[PDB]
Amino acid sequence: QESTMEMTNAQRLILSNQYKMMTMLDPANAERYRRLQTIIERGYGLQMRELDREFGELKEETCRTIIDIMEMYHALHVSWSNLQDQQSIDERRVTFLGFDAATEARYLGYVRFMVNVEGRYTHFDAGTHGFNAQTPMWEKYQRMLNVWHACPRQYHLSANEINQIINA
Amino acid sequence: QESTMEMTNAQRLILSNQYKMMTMLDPANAERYRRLQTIIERGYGLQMRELDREFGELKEETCRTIIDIMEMYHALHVSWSNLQDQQSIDERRVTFLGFDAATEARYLGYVRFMVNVEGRYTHFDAGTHGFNAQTPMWEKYQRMLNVWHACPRQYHLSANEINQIINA
Amino acid sequence: QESTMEMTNAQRLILSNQYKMMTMLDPANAERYRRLQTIIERGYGLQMRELDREFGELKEETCRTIIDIMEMYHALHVSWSNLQDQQSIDERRVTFLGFDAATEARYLGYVRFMVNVEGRYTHFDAGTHGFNAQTPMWEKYQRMLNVWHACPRQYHLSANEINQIINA
Amino acid sequence: QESTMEMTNAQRLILSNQYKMMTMLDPANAERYRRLQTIIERGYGLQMRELDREFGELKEETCRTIIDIMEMYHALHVSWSNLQDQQSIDERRVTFLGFDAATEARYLGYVRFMVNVEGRYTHFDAGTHGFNAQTPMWEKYQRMLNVWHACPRQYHLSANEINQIINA
Amino acid sequence: QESTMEMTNAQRLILSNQYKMMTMLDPANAERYRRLQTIIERGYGLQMRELDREFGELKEETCRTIIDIMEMYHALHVSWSNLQDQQSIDERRVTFLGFDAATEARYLGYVRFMVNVEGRYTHFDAGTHGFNAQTPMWEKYQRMLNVWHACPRQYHLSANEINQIINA
Amino acid sequence: QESTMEMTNAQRLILSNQYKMMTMLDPANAERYRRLQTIIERGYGLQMRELDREFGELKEETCRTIIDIMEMYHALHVSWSNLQDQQSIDERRVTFLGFDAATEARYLGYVRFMVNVEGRYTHFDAGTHGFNAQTPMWEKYQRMLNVWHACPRQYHLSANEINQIINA
Amino acid sequence: QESTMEMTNAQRLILSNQYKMMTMLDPANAERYRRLQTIIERGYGLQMRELDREFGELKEETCRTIIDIMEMYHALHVSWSNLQDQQSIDERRVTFLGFDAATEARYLGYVRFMVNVEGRYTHFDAGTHGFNAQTPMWEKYQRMLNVWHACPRQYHLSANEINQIINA
Amino acid sequence: QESTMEMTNAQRLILSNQYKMMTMLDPANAERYRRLQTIIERGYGLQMRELDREFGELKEETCRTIIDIMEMYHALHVSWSNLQDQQSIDERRVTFLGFDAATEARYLGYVRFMVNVEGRYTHFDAGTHGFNAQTPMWEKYQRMLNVWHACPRQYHLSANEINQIINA
Amino acid sequence: QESTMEMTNAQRLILSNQYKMMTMLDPANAERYRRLQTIIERGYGLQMRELDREFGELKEETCRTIIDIMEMYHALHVSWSNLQDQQSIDERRVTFLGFDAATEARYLGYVRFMVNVEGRYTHFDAGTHGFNAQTPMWEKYQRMLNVWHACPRQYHLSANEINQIINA
Amino acid sequence: QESTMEMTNAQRLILSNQYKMMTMLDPANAERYRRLQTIIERGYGLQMRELDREFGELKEETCRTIIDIMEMYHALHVSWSNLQDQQSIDERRVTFLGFDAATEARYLGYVRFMVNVEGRYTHFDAGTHGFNAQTPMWEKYQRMLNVWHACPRQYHLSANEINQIINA
Amino acid sequence: QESTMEMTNAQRLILSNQYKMMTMLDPANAERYRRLQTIIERGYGLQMRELDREFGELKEETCRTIIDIMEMYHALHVSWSNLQDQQSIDERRVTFLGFDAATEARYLGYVRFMVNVEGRYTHFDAGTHGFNAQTPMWEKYQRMLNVWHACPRQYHLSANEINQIINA
Amino acid sequence: QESTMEMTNAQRLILSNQYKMMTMLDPANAERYRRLQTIIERGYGLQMRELDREFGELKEETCRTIIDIMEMYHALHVSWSNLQDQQSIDERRVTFLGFDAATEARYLGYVRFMVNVEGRYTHFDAGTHGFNAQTPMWEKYQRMLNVWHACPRQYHLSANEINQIINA
Ligand SMILES: [Cl-]
Ligand SMILES: [Cl-]
Ligand SMILES: [Cl-]
Ligand SMILES: [Cl-]
Ligand SMILES: [Cl-]
Ligand SMILES: [Cl-]
Ligand SMILES: [Cl-]
Ligand SMILES: [Cl-]
Ligand SMILES: [Cl-]
Ligand SMILES: [Cl-]
Ligand SMILES: [Cl-]
Ligand SMILES: [Cl-]
Ligand SMILES: [Cl-]
Ligand SMILES: [Cl-]
Ligand SMILES: [Cl-]
Ligand SMILES: [Cl-]
Ligand SMILES: [Cl-]
Ligand SMILES: [Cl-]
Ligand SMILES: [Cl-]
Ligand SMILES: [Cl-]
Ligand SMILES: [Cl-]
Ligand SMILES: [Cl-]
Ligand SMILES: [Cl-]
Ligand SMILES: [Cl-]
Ligand SMILES: [Cl-]
Ligand SMILES: [Cl-]
Ligand SMILES: [Cl-]
Ligand SMILES: [Cl-]
Ligand SMILES: [Cl-]
Ligand SMILES: [Cl-]
């Protein structure tokens, strides 16, 4: 992530040409494109920095971690569903509840992208709030994962294994 | 701002392709785009320098200072009009006058951008010449800012404070 | 090749703009474009790496070696046909057979691009599988090329020369 | 400057998207665009090198020098046309003849650009081959420029000054 | 600190021998040990990363700060219990409440360690969730510590000093 | 990986001690332990290199790619079974076949570890040879993954999508 | 290996002289020698690279591994023949089969050099194809060597040991 | 290309011995060999530098470019020969005429080497001057190649394609 | 001595595994080992610093100097008791007295190690307090050594020499 | 080989724990383990250096050289045994006699390890002194090897070849 | 110095040409030459190492020292042969005895070279083993040289000077 | 000039092979070549230094200066003999005399090389001793050159100029 302010003159010309094309292709938004064209041509620094703030980052390992959490709960729920006596293990406890909108919006956004766009885990119960847990869940999932990955087998888990993971 | 003359061949190819697409989208200007396409393909250095001259720079801090000066006049004017007592302060002195066209062109442009494009400060009395002061003002404004920001309350100024500011 | 994850913010904006333009030009595929736009804007690292995987490399020297092998077989086949007569050399021996789909896919792909897109060597007998030899050939061809280029004349080969080449 | 083979994956993706867009806009040439898209996507080094050869360079100073030579002939010819005794100074010797098509192609290309595209020196006599002098002129013009710029005044030249220049 | 993936072959062999020994000593868990032995012997990068996540860090200064906060509450509460007019200073406000289980887990873990394992501050009231305050406290405690350490004497505090601290 | 030959003297002592302990714990195998103890103590370089050869590596990204390929086949097989109906797509096409024992042994080994030890993908039809495809697959799977990840939704695939993937 | 294109002028002269001497000694092949002399003297870069391709490398450790594999099979076969009796271990299992001509040509070539030129292992049953296994073996042999060198004694192996080795 | 003057003493001894051998092998030229022996032994610097001038260089890409030009004309001539109406396209225009002896002797020498020694393109008409064009042809061929390689197919070219290439 | 806090994750894992094995071997101390296991797994920095404080250092040269001082007293005592003449030298002065517990603790420890563990100097008269001098002695001993080693014969000293040594 | 004195605190703790375990596992040697534990904990430098002297080094090439010497004598003896007239070649001369205990103990130790532990060359006559030659043999074997490896075939050697090797 | 494995491709080609020439000149040994040609062409690392061992080094200073020792004995023996009372100084003690064949082979080799090839010190008595002293002499001779060169005159030595030298 | 002692083992091998070939070609000198072969194979440093001393150096500029001095005398002599007037200039003074054998040996050698081998200046009056001046002349010649080259015409000198030159 290098800043737009550091872009080269060639990159400025490339962008400028795109804004001119976008006005041709989408005249309803010419006001926006002409404004951006001015910012880029004149090199208005405040507005260029404000452009940086439109680009985010979610590291590859963080993405992978969020997916692994969902896989863990698939593992937990399958294992649970296939128990005989479910030892008072409440189903709500082997259900992925997601992440916090205030504090973990990047994570929650990623969950929604994996389900709604990529179409993964479409059988998971989102609740009535689309995986907003409304309390932070990151550090807790990290404890669960540490226990889960320490099981000598991660799928077809015993009730005890399930309890150790949900309890972490 | 790295010169267009230092662009990579991938960037030349990207620009070349844009000029072709621009021709497709806006055939009426085919001559203009074909000319630019030739300059970029042939790497005509003189014309590439001329392209560089189309791209300006207004540093982020300078944009912020222009905005601050306008905010300062908002404070001064709101303070002035709220003075129960008069002290016979002229309104022209508590009114933002703008920048010098001849030697402050980047600054006057930015004011006009902030007003007409971003929509900020639209209640300010523009010039007879749309914020073209005609005297150089940067140095002055700087003196006024230094005083304004030294007031422990920057808004709802007293007449003493108003006068300290405009006199700097 | 530098990874998409290292791209600059100007490059993210160029790309984002492209996906916006592609939606305007081809709303049928807006789902595809919007998804990519999101990956680029939010900087989703896992999906960005996946994008990396769409981009191959076949070094120039490797390209040239594949063409050289085809040229070698041209030389071999003309030489073998022009033989006052041919000393029980089977024509299959002096016929370019191609590359292994499984372990030599990039090489096979280039063969097909050179014949099918560039139009070179169109008179070569393609396989019953369009130059899929179904066994690795790269190492064999290198041994053949070494003998071929050691022949003081490389076209109009003697049957001794032809045999030394094919038995390499 | 950086060969196309050095382009980043971001630049490859940008180029690939342009070929997709150009196909949407200009389906008659879809073959050309798809071929390029393949080269860029697969990283076919030999074809990427060939792309490099489409891009030239003519240094800013060399551009200026070509223009200066034309201006010199303008100075010479105007000067000649106010001489009373034009001596036996032939007009052809104060006529810009151009550059060698075979060995000075980039220089001849730029003269043609300057006259035909930019519209400068349109009153110059182009002769019978559009400023192709058919013999190398660069070194000669350099000798002439050296004498011309050593004149304390460069316009309204004396006949002595003219002969000194053209004989250089 | 160095991930397990960076360990030397000597360290791998040491770890492999430990798993062999642990199997000799604890054959009931041979499955767990043999699985780890495989991961280490084969260098399975993904499982080695997962091992990394079993190891945490809590910087020496952060440990000391947690202890200091507890000591501060000790100072406050002792001080409060020798006040004549305890003002309407509620005892709960000079009671250490702990840390947030969800967002300050490492901090809550350390309090619990210090009390339950090291046996310090055993007379502290742990409340109804074993020092889980259920809301982030770190920043608050930092403000309190700042006032407390600015007292010329930190023990046998005045009511004014107490209120200054707790209101921080 | 750093070679056992580069180990420090502290590491040699740790290892030597281990072999001594293993003899105490498992005198049945004292011959093995004592031999290793001698190699380490005397620093016998040839045998130390041989020890190096016991330690493999399979990079984390490689691990993840193998799992991703299995997940791709899961997606393909569910999609193919959920088809309102299936357009003569043979199920063998959408069945994970594994890796080549001869040239892909590390990959095959990981597949087996993930199924047999971790318990993942236990419902996959293993071969008549437990995922030994008996022909190289790595390159094929990469081509499939590239198509799969370019599908805006990756689960619940259309038969067009399924075909594009399998024919890659 | 440094390329012939980087050779010094003294090295070009040494080489040129050699080709001159070879012509004097063997005028029958003067055409070959003179051609090489020209390539070296004129420094024809393409043909010089072709010369590079005549020179292989097989690292010393690789040489030694091939010999070690043959020695392993010697140990296996003697052990298997000396068995008081043999537990249905097929002799083909304990017979060195060689390397794959297609993908393992350097290895196969060294096997043949060691037997046919150095005279080592002349009692080994060569193939029906002189140690061309016609399938890749390098990875298999490495797995076998790892087991063999972990045997405290490597000659006079038990049938358990023999089986562990061959099944690796 | 490092100079003979920088050669090491070992290289001097090697050369000296070769000159002694060459006198034995070719006594008719002993005068030459004894002279060179003296130059090398005494390290006569002027004469050593004069040796440098016997070694040339023609870069690999330049070699490849010259061959590609010949291939282009093979492409042009085949395409031409297979037209129905050859649209007044003069055969002399799709015939490779070669290079200039004065200015491009290295290039012309390479053409002669490829045809006379390597035996390639033996069906090309050399003219009566063995591919001496007697005017510079390099920059022009570069234009032709740029057009040729921009054709979406390079062989079996239309008349228009042929005209665009020959016209460049 | 690199701090425990800087240990690698492989070293954390090694230590963790030791504490588990220690529990297996010495279950009575399970609480102590489990505590250390937690410190190491969680990376509790304060407790890890405390671990560092358990490890000391006595430089090799300092150990050698302690031993030399004891050897010096052996020489002095053997010399003294061999004096035919008396010269009334007290035996206490020719008897090694040890080191100061309070400020020379590392030194007194090493004497006690050398005597009680290594078994050296077991005939020396230990203290009433086992070589605890109670006055600091290092500096003194250093003065005595300097004199002793300046005697051309270090053993079978004269009374003059003995006195020179003890008086320093 | 880095010294024990440079070991890290983590390595000290690892060693300390091993000595505590070893006392549990081998109480008869607790005296030794407790002593080493003290040395490591207190960092007694003299004793730590004395630990270094327990670790040796025999480079991989030296190991390989010793084995090659034994192989050479296998080669010599087989060749000899298969001669018809053994030309007064004394069998003692084609028998490996080993190395010198005083001067070459590392080498002799390696021979004994290869035969007694690894079980190689078990048919060799050790003499009555287990391969102690009692005179240095290293430099001589180097001469033998140089000759042996210069034979164009190393096995099935003529009598002359045998004599040249034994004579070196 | 640079091992053969490091040689450049130019050096490989030079060596290959020599083997070809040596075969032309000495066809009786074609087998030897062709074998070496193969090793060099294929870059067989193990055989290239073996070539390295054919080349030794004896530093210039070590050569000079050997000669100096001989000269010293010349000085001693001449000096002895002009003594009147030769004391009971035995002549054998002023006779150069040589060097140890087993441990000082390079030194013994050089004496033999100097006497037998260069013809120096031919009047020296070589004894019964051609200057093989059968015991290491290097260190002794160094002590002698030290005394000899400390004589203010080194020739026409006194008997005292002689005994001082030989007793060194 | 890097010493022979620093040659690489490839260069030792090349030299060794030359001495073998030299023996084949010139068997009468076998003793001389075998001696050199031994020096090079054994790396006898003293004899290798002696080889270095066989190779000289005469810098290019020094060769050029010698030639210039001879050219200067050509100019002087041609000028002298063309003097219509005499001015009684002696011919000896306008005649090149050569260089000093004792202290200018490299210079006299080069003159003799230029005359007798290159054939330059063959009309010059050689000495009674073939250009051996017997007085050192370099410094003188330098003075004469400085004057000669300061004459604006270097040939067809006047008597004034001739005298200025010879007198320097
Ligand atoms: Cl589920
Ligand atoms: Cl674009
Ligand atoms: Cl306002
Ligand atoms: Cl207002
Ligand atoms: Cl005020
Ligand atoms: Cl044909
Ligand atoms: Cl870019
Ligand atoms: Cl230029
Ligand atoms: Cl004009
Ligand atoms: Cl005019
Ligand atoms: Cl360690
Ligand atoms: Cl922390
Ligand atoms: Cl308390
Ligand atoms: Cl209290
Ligand atoms: Cl399914
Ligand atoms: Cl057998
Ligand atoms: Cl043709
Ligand atoms: Cl351990
Ligand atoms: Cl004593
Ligand atoms: Cl005593
Ligand atoms: Cl004394
Ligand atoms: Cl044997
Ligand atoms: Cl060389
Ligand atoms: Cl030496
Ligand atoms: Cl003598
Ligand atoms: Cl004598
Ligand atoms: Cl040679
Ligand atoms: Cl003359
Ligand atoms: Cl003359
Ligand atoms: Cl004059």
Image: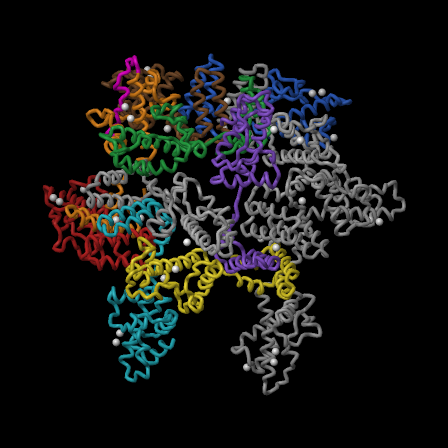
Chain colours: A yellow, C purple, E cyan, G green, I red, J orange, K brown, L blue
Between K40 and L103, which is closer to the camera in this rendering?
K40
Magenta region, main secondary structure? loop
Q: Quadrant of ligand 20?
A: top left
Quadrant where the C terminus of chain K sits is top left
Q: Is residue K23 above or below residue C139?
A: above
Quadrant where the N terminus of chain K sits is top left
Between C41 and J28, which is closer to the camera in this rendering?
C41
Residue L53 percent location from the top left of the image: 48, 24
Between A155 and L28, which is closer to the camera in this rendering?
A155
Residue E111 painted magenta: no
Q: Is residue G37 visible?
A: no
Query: For the point 38% across and 21% down, which residue is it?
Result: J151
Residue J100 painted magenta: yes
Q: Is residue G113 above or below residue L23?
A: below
Residue G40, image quadrant: top right
Q: Which residues are magenta?
A: J83-102
Q: Is residue E143 left or right of residue I37?
A: right
Residue C118, image quadrant: top right
Q: Is residue E102 left or right of residue E117?
A: right
Residue K19 percent location from the top left of the image: 47, 22
Between E120 and K142, which is closer to the camera in this rendering?
E120
